[PDB]
Image (tube, coloured by chain):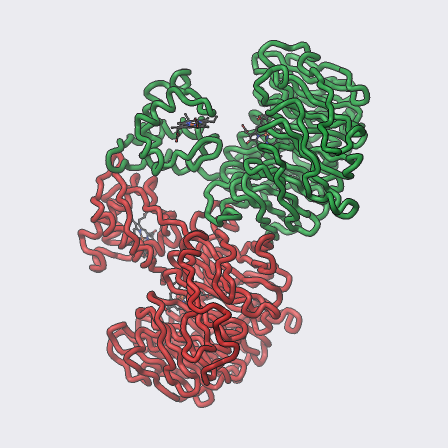
Chain colours: A red, B green
C-alpha cells in the first residue's frame, strides 16, 4: 500500500550519458524505464531514489552493487518487502534489465513547481462577483455525498436521502479525496496529479468555478475551520515537490508555498523528500495541521499572517500518514504507521502530548472513530492494515485522567488489511472494513461492534459481519469493500464496493438502526468508487 | 567520493577518478563564489544549461586567463595546472556534483567537551578585567588573542578554527564563543585561571555566524550557529555545545516564491524582547525569529523581508532589528517585540554594509542608526524612534560622503560624540589605511555634507609595507577608546591602533609577532550587551 506516482511517470526526460563502468540507454529505453520507475518504484524508493520504505537506489550505492545484483533483486525480490517483479511476471525480463541499467544511471531530476507555474495553471472560471449570492438549486447540500470515481478522474455528487446521482463531474485525472469549506458551500477536490478543483454547490448546476495545480503528485487538501475564518483559505499538500500551498478560499489564488524539505526529528539528518500526508484544520486556533511523513514532523501553520508566518514544528514520529481530531476537536491523533504509533497533539497549546504504540501492525485510521465507551469514557479508535486488531485510546485528559492517551483495549475484527473504521454520535455501532484482505469473503465484508455492549473487562467484543459485496450482488472480479461514511443524521452508513474499472462496482447503504441492507447504488458511470464524503460530516469534522 | 555523472551529446565524460579530482578543486576553490550547487553568487551560475552553450573553449580560456570583474586567473597564475584547468572545463560541462550534508551524526562526532561544566570554576579564578577584554581574530593563524582593554597586554593567544570570523559572548560574559569560516566552533571559559577551549564542535563545511541567548532569564542557556553550507542553523547547549536542534534553511524565495537549494545563513542576533534568535536567510530573503523555549515543539516566525540579507543590528532601544539586504540596497526593519516586518527602505547608496551599525542621537533627527557602504562613499541615517519621532521613523533622513568607497564598518558609543567610518576595501592605500570621523554634536541635518576628520590609522601604526587595510572600530567598556585593526598579510607586519575618543589622538599601538592578520575585535562588555 505505497504510492504510485503515475503523473511523474508521464513526464518525458532527457536520457543521461553513462559514466565509467556503466552502459547507456537510448532516450527511448531510458524513458521506458523512467515510466516504470515512477509508476511502480518511486513510492517505496523515493522520487529522488534517496529511499523511503525501500533502500536508497542512488548511483553512489547501486554502482557498487553492480548490474547483476540489481537484476537479481528486481527479478526475485526479497522477503523484507521488495516485490518479485521478474518471477511474478509484473515486469518482463527486458523491463527488469531496463530498470537495473536505469538504477545505475544518473537519477532523473523531476522539476520543481513554484509560484510562476502555479499562477500559470490558475484559472478562475466564475469570479466570486458572478457567483450566486444564495443557493439556487433545491438540493439538500448538507446531506450530499461527494464520491471519488477513481480511474475515471471524476466525482459523483449523490443525494443522501434519495440516493440519486445528481451529477458526475470531470477533473481530467484521478481524484483522491473531497473536502468542504466550513460554510459547506465550496467543494474542494485534490487530484493525484496535484490539480485542485473548487466547486460552487450553490449553482443551479454545480461545477468547477476555479482550478489550480500545486505540484506533480498530491493526495491532501483541507479548508480553514477556525470560527471566524470560514471560506478564507484552502491548503493542499504534495508528495512532489515536497511542499504545501495555502490558497485563497474563494479564488484558489496561491498565497504561500512552504517547502517541507528538512531534518528528520530523531536522527536529525537532512531529508530531501518529505511527503505531506494528512492535513487537518484546527478548531481552536486559525491554523492548519500538516503531517510531514518522512521527517516525522507535524506543523501547526497559522494563517492569520502569511507574510510574517508563524508555525510550530512539532517533533513527532516518522512515517506519519492519516489521523483525526478527538470528539472535542482539541487533540489531533495520527498514525506514524510504520512504527505502529499514535501521536497525540494538543492543538490548543500547540504541543505534543503523547506517543503510544497500538500493539498492532500498521495502524490506518483514516480520520478514526470517536465515541464514548460505556466504561472507559471518550475514546478514539483505529483499525490496522497489518493485522485484524482495533485499538482504543482514551481522549479525555480532564474527565478520565488515568485513561487519557493510553491504549485501553485492543480486539480483533474481520481480519488484516483494514483501512477504515467508522461511527457517528447518533449511532451505537462501530464499523470496520478489511479492504486489502486476500480473502474475498473478508475483503467484501464489514465488521460491526455494538458500542453499548462494550464492557471494560478485557474480553474481545463480538461483532456482526455484514456481507456488503454480496448485498450488492457483485461477485465478478476483485470487489473490495472500503470506507464507511454516514449521512447527515447518522442514520445510514455507506460503503464502496470497489471493483475493477471494466467491472461492476456499487455503493451500499446500510440502515444503521437495523444493520440491514437499505439501498444499492449502481450506475454505468459508477467507475471504481472509493472515497465518499458527506458534506455536513466533512465540513464539521463529525467522526 | 561522489558518483561521476554521465556526459550528454557532444560533451566529454570524466572517469570517477578524474571527476572526483575536479570535484575537490571545485568545492575548495570555486564553490565560495559560484555556489555549492553552481547556481551562482558572487560569480555567475555555472550550471550545464549555461556552460554547454558557452562551450569547452570559452570555459577553458576563462579559467586560465580569468577576467577583471573578480574571476581569478587560475591557469596563468599557476594555481591550477593546464590539466586541472581542462579537467575543470569538462567538469563545468557535466551535471553539478552532489554536496555532502552535515547532520547530527557528523556534529556529535566532532563534538568534544574538554572540561565538563561540573569541573569548571564556580567563580572567576584569574585576575583579569573580563568585561574590558578584547577578543581579536588572528585570521590566517587560526587563533584569537585576548587583550587587556586598559593595559593593552596580550593576556593569551588561543588556538581556534581557521580564520575565525567573529567572537560572541554569553549574556553573563563568562563564555566566549568563536566560529571559523570552516564551521568549527570553540567555547572558551573566561573564568579559568588559564582560559581555554572547554568545548568544541563543527556545524557545517562553511560558516560565518554564531550568537548567544540574550533574553533576560535565558543567560548562558543557548548558543546558535549558522552555516553557509549546508544551508542550516543549529541551536546548541550554552554550557556544553551539545547540538540540540538543526534546522534546514532550504526553502522558497519570499517574492517570486520559487524553491532555492542554497539559502545561506547570514547574520544571527538575539532578541532582548522575547526568548528568540534572529536569523537572516540570505538567498530567500527570510528573517527567522526562532523561539528557544521549546526545541521539540518549535515556534518560529518566518518573516518575508528582502533578498540578499547579510548583516545588521538592533536599534538603541534593542527592539528593532535593522538589516542590510545588500545587493538590493535596502534596509529591512523588523519589530522583535511584535514579530513583524515594519519597513524596507532604499539607502540611496550602493551595497549597504553596516556590520551591527551605529546607533546615536542625532541633534536634529533624534535617535538614528547609521550604515556606510561597500559600493560608494555614502553614510545613510535611518530614524529609529516611532514613539518620540514618528515622522522620522524608518525613513532615510540623510546621506553624506565619508572617505571613499569600500567601507565595511561604522561605529560609535553612547559616551562618544564621534561617528567613525572605515574604508577597508578601497583600492587606494591612503584611503584604506585611514578612518573618517564625524562630530555628531555638529550635525544639523540641513542637507549639507558634514565635515569629517581623517585619522591616518595605518600611518600611526608605522606600517607602509604591503598596504595594510584598516578595519572595524570597536570601543572599550567605558566607551572612551576605540580600536582599529591594521590588517596586513600573514607574512607581513600588522598592528592594532587604539584611539583616544575624547581627543581623536593616538593612544597606543599594539604590535606583537603573534599578532598575525588581525581582523575582527570584540570587547566583552559591548558584545554581551549589544552596545553599538
Ligand atoms: C495523504 C493521504 C490521505 C490524507 C488526505 C487528507 O488528509 O486530506 C489519504 C486519505 C484517504 C482517504 C480518506 C478518508 C477519510 O475518511 O478521511 C480515502 C478514502 C483514501 C482512499 C485511498 N487511498 Fe489514500 N493513499 C495515499 C495517500 C493519502 N490518502 C497514498 O499515498 C496511497 C497509500 C497510495 C497512493 O498511490 O495514493 C493511498 C491509497 C489509497 C487507496 O488505495 C484508496 C483506498 C482508494 C483510492 O482512491 O486510491 N485515502
Ligand atoms: C554572515 C556574516 C557576518 C555576520 C556574522 C554574525 O552575525 O555573527 C559577518 C560579520 C563580520 C564581522 C562583524 C563585525 C561586527 O562588528 O559585528 C567581521 C569583523 C567580519 C570580517 C570579515 N568579513 Fe564577514 N564575511 C561574510 C559573512 C559574514 N560576515 C562573507 O560572506 C564575506 C562577504 C566573504 C568571505 O570571504 O567570507 C565576508 C567577508 C569578511 C572579510 O573580508 C573580513 C573583513 C575578514 C575575514 O576574515 O573574512 N565579518
Ligand atoms: C515497496 C512495496 C517497494 C516497491 C514497490 C519496490 N521496492 Fe525495491 N525494495 C523495497 C525494499 C523494502 C527493499 C529492501 C528489501 C530487503 O531485503 O532489505 C527493496 C530493495 C530493492 C533493491 C535492492 C537494494 C539494495 O539491496 O541495496 C533494488 C535494486 C530494488 N528494490 C529495485 C526496485 C525497483 C526497480 C522497483 C520498481 C520496479 C522496486 N524496487 C519496487 C521495497 C519496494
Ligand atoms: C570569487 C573570488 C571567484 C572564484 C574563487 C572563482 N570565480 Fe569563477 N568567476 C567569478 C566572477 C565574478 C566571474 C565573472 C567575471 C566577469 O568578468 O564577469 C566568474 C566567471 C567564471 C566563469 C565564466 C562564466 C561566464 O562567463 O558565464 C567560469 C567558467 C568560472 N568563473 C569558473 C571558475 C572555476 C572553475 C573556479 C575554481 C577554480 C572559479 N571560477 C573560481 C568569481 C570567482
Ligand atoms: C489512503 N490511505
Ligand atoms: C563581513 N561582512
Measuring from the top left, give residue B187's x and y in whole percent.
64, 32
* Residue B350, visible in the rendered structure: yes
Task: Relative to A60, say whether A348 is above or below.
Answer: below
Q: Nearer the viewer, residue A392 or A306?
A: A306
* Residue A72, visible in the rendered structure: no
Task: Relative to A23, say whether A179 is above or below.
Answer: below
Task: Relative to B520, say whether A336 is above or below.
Answer: below
Total marks shown come to 0
Q: Residue at x 75, y 21 (%)?
A: B148
Task: Relative to A168, say whether B504 is above or below.
Answer: above
Measuring from the top left, give residue B287's x and y in whole percent.
59, 45
Picture quadrant of residue B516: top right
Measuring from the top left, give residue B288's x and y in whole percent.
60, 46
Q: Is residue A297 left or right of residue B470?
A: left
Measuring from the top left, give residue A26's x and y in whole percent.
20, 44
Picture quadrant of residue B75: top left
Q: Nearer the viewer, residue A307 or A262?
A: A307
Q: Residue at x 57, y 19 (%)?
A: B427
Picture quadrant of residue A471: bottom left
Image quarter where the N terminus of chain A lies is bottom left
Q: Is residue A165 left or right of residue A143?
A: left
Amino acid at each position: 500500500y505505497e504510492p504510485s506516482l503515475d503523473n511523474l511517470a508521464q513526464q518525458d526526460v532527457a536520457a543521461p550519458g553513462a559514466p565509467e563502468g556503466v552502459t547507456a540507454l537510448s532516450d527511448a529505453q531510458y524513458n521506458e524505464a523512467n515510466k516504470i520507475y515512477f509508476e511502480r518504484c518511486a513510492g517505496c524508493h523515493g522520487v529522488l531514489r534517496k529511499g523511503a520504505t525501500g533502500k536508497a537506489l542512488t548511483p553512489d550505492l547501486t554502482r557498487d552493487l553492480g548490474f547483476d545484483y540489481l537484476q537479481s533483486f528486481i527479478t526475485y525480490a526479497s522477503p523484507a518487502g521488495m516485490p518479485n517483479w521478474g518471477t511474478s511476471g509484473e515486469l518482463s525480463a527486458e523491463q527488469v534489465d531496463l530498470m537495473a541499467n536505469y538504477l545505475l544511471l544518473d537519477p532523473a531530476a523531476p522539476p520543481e513547481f513554484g509560484m510562476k507555474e502555479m499562477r500559470e495553471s490558475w484559472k478562475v472560471h466564475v469570479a466570486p462577483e458572478d457567483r450566486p449570492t444564495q443557493q439556487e438549486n433545491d438540493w439538500d447540500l448538507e446531506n450530499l455525498f461527494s464520491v471519488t470515481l477513481r480511474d475515471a478522474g471524476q466525482i459523483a455528487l449523490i443525494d443522501g436521502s434519495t440516493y440519486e446521482i445528481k451529477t458526475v463531474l470531470d477533473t481530467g485525472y484521478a481524484v483522491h479525496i473531497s473536502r468542504l469549506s466550513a460554510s459547506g458551500r465550496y467543494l474542494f477536490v485534490i487530484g493525484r496529479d496535484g490539480k485542485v478543483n473548487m466547486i460552487d454547490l450553490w449553482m443551479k448546476e454545480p461545477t468547477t468555478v476555479a482550478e489550480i495545480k500545486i505540484g506533480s503528485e498530491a493526495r491532501s487538501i483541507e479548508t480553514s475551520k477556525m470560527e471566524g475564518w470560514e471560506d478564507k483559505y484552502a491548503i493542499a499538500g504534495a508528495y512532489w515537490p515536497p511542499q504545501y500551498v495555502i490558497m485563497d478560499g474563494e479564488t484558489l489564488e496561491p498565497k504561500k508555498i512552504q517547502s517541507t524539505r528538512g531534518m528528520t526529528y530523531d536522527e536529525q539528518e537532512y531529508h530531501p523528500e518529505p511527503r505531506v500526508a494528512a492535513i487537518l484544520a484546527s478548531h481552536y486556533r486559525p491554523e492548519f495541521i500538516v503531517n510531514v511523513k518522512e521527517t516525522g514532523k507535524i506543523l501547526l501553520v497559522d494563517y492569520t499572517d502569511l507574510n510574517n508566518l508563524k508555525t510550530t514544528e512539532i517533533s513527532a514520529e516518522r512515517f506519519l500518514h492519516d489521523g483525526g481530531l478527538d470528539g472535542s476537536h482539541r487533540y489531533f491523533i495520527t498514525a506514524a504507521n510504520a512504527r505502529n504509533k499514535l501521536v497525540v497533539i494538543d492543538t490548543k497549546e500547540g504541543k505534543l502530548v503523547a506517543i503510544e504504540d497500538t500493539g498492532g501492525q500498521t495502524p490506518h485510521p483514516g480520520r478514526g472513530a470517536n465515541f464514548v465507551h460505556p466504561t472507559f469514557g471518550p475514546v478514539w479508535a483505529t483499525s490496522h492494515m497489518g493485522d485484524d486488531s482495533v485499538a482504543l485510546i482514551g481522549t479525555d485528559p480532564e474527565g478520565h485522567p488515568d485513561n487519557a492517551w493510553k491504549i485501553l483495549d485492543s480486539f480483533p475484527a474481520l481480519g488484516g488489511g483494514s483501512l477504515f473504521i467508522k461511527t457517528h454520535p447518533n449511532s451505537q455501532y462501530l464499523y470496520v472494513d478489511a479492504t486489502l484482505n486476500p480473502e474475498a469473503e473478508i475483503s467484501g465484508s464489514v465488521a460491526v461492534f455494538d458500542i453499548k455492549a462494550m464492557t471494560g473487562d478485557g474480553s474481545d467484543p463480538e461483532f456482526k459481519t455484514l456481507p456488503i459485496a454480496e448485498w450488492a450482488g457483485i461477485t465478478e472480479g476483485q470487489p473490495r469493500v472500503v470506507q464507511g461514511e454516514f449521512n447527515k443524521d447518522g442514520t445510514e452508513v455507506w460503503f464502496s464496493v470497489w471493483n475493477g474499472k471494466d467491472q461492476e462496482s456499487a455503493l451500499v447503504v446500510v440502515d444503521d438502526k437495523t444493520l440491514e441492507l437499505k439501498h444499492v447504488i449502481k450506475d454505468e458511470r459508477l467507475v471504481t468508487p472509493t472515497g465518499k464524503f458527506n458534506v455536513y460530516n466533512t465540513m464539521t469534522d463529525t467522526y
